[PDB]
Amino acid sequence: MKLYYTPGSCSLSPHIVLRETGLDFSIERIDLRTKKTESGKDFLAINPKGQVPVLQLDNGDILTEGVAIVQYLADLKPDRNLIAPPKALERYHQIEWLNFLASEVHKGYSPLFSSDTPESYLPVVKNKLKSKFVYINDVLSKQKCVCGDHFTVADAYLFTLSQWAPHVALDLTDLSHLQDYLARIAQRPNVHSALVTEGLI
Amino acid sequence: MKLYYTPGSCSLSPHIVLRETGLDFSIERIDLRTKKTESGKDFLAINPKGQVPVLQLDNGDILTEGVAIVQYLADLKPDRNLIAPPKALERYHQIEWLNFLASEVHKGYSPLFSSDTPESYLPVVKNKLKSKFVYINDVLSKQKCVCGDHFTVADAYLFTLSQWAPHVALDLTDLSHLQDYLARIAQRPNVHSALVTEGLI
Ligand SMILES: *SC[C@H](NC(=O)CC[C@H](N)C(=O)O)C(=O)NCC(=O)O
Ligand SMILES: *SC[C@H](NC(=O)CC[C@H](N)C(=O)O)C(=O)NCC(=O)O
Image (cartoon, rainbow over all chains, first blue to last red; front, side, top):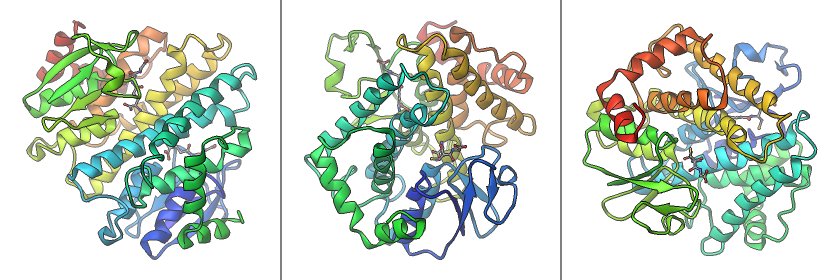
């Protein structure tokens, strides 16, 4: 099981999940500029969409899209409780949150990382994004995690998306519930070890 | 089971799926401008995020996010084959496509429907979007549907997202594989009947 990643990218989410499940895996750094693996192979041949994360299964199959990857992983180790059982109501609310984070938050960052974005539009984009974290902050005021009382794959995803905030000058320091939650998630051995292995920390 | 929708919106996807599964449901039109149901109730009390689709379950629970809604629906009628069984490999590739459509295509339209978007940025956004459909078109050249040989919930979603193309002057007429696929999907009784019931056709 190999994970194609780029340090500090959205591939940190499946990286955290891989450690939290205790599965046997290997990672391979991808260079998003040249689209080449650290071993010199063409990454477009692996994933035509040219992005990370990408999970290579032991049988050879390739899986793209982070939300699909973390569900496949968590489903392999039911006993970890990183996702609810299939067909359970709690599972659909998790899927619901994974989609909210992928389309509203994750994709909300995109224009802030693009060079072709009008400097006059940046303020507008940043505000749309903060309104998203404000919603998340309100939710974290009556519960310990985004989907409930325990740590799930959606939490791994949110910690990852929160990390970028400083790099694009998005202020989230007024969101104390979110700030306390981030601090907690960061002291988890499996999360901390993921950051170390990637060169952050 | 009630579906909160707006004619021709992204809520057409779960609408098509509800008919394809043959479940007992009702629909209620939402006014996105005033955020009020057609029965005069405050929609923000139902869905704080203020968007459609929204599915009200018989037990009272509320489900948001289209990708979560269509999975919950299809999972209720395994025999229809609108999604693969949970934990099956085919299921994760479907989840993978549902995420691609939600974050890369669906969210890719967003700036084209916003009034606060610089007219100079529109060309850039449109091109990013077409590159997405070009990828989808290539895929449809060696298979009948987006995820395989049969009709799944991801197909209901793509037909829905393709419908908007003309309204934002996005040309997809050079994508013959996509054009033939759309024509096929449209002649399905359950899809056709969804369009009629919504005022399109
Ligand atoms: S975070 C790094 C970028 N990945 C994605 O945007 C993944 C999007 C998928 N829809 C998903 O996994 O959810 C990335 O690798 N971008 C490539 C680049 O060239 O910047
Ligand atoms: S398509 C109509 C709009 N819905 C969404 O954007 C849903 C986004 C979710 N992430 C999802 O369901 O996938 C909508 O209702 N917009 C509200 C408005 O005021 O325009």
